[PDB]
Image 1 (cartoon, rainbow, N blue to C red):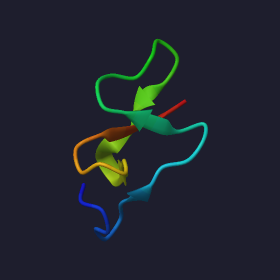
Image 2 (cartoon, rainbow, N blue to C red):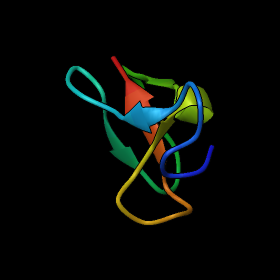
Image 3 (tube, rainbow, N blue to C red):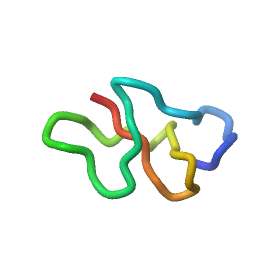
Image 4 (cartoon, one colour):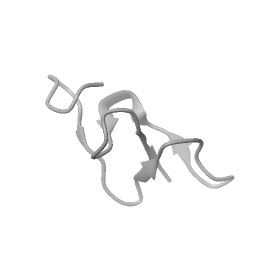
Length: 45
C-alpha cells in the first residue's frame, strides 16, 4: 500500500519493518501497513 492510502498506515509492535521477509515468528502484514520507505512491507507478530 501507499504511504497515506485509505486503509493503510504506519505499522506498530508487535509489528515491525521488513523489506525482505518476516522472521520465523511474525507474519507479513504489509497489506495495510507500509514502512518509511515506499517499498518495505510492515510485518506483524
